[PDB]
Image (cartoon, rainbow, N blue to C red; front, top):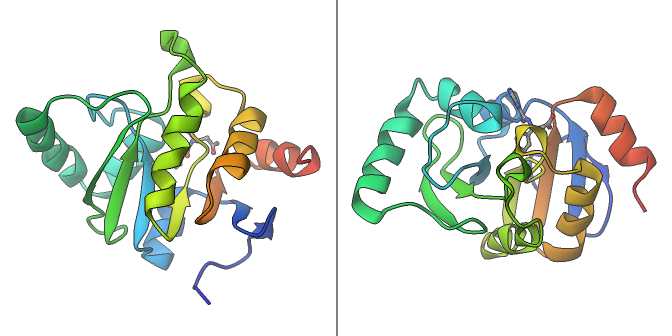
Length: 167
Ligand SMILES: O=C(O)C[C@H](NC(=O)c1ncnc2[nH]ccc12)c1ccc(Cl)cc1
């Protein structure tokens, strides 16, 4: 039993809800919130910009130190950093950006990072400003993640389409 509330159950292990991931994190304080990161951990916009703003830029400060030490992530890769005021940990996951021409097959590799954590709050990877079809992202999620994932879909219109078309 966990504190996630109001989710629709898509599968044994995948759940979905129309919610702002920022507001959801402040309420649940999950062990792991997933960020829709880029390889540079530059959290300028999208989900990443929203999460970072909610941390008063502390996420960005920590991220800049991480990059200065370790260099950029790989597309499809991830790192665990602090969750600041939003969660215990933030799993920064880099899905491919279609608006950068990156291979959508890398989306499955990106979701595989979720399997290292028993429970996560997460967005649909590669959706939004990353350019991928969110219906495809939800499918890859369900077919790749085996741990318990609570998806927040910010757009109510997108949420209803994801649910109504979910196979
Ligand atoms: O679920 C959605 O609609 C799409 C989602 N976007 C957000 O979560 C979002 N975007 C902008 N401002 C925001 N403020 C609070 C949340 C939020 C998204 C998913 C993957 C990527 Cl790669 C990029 C964006």
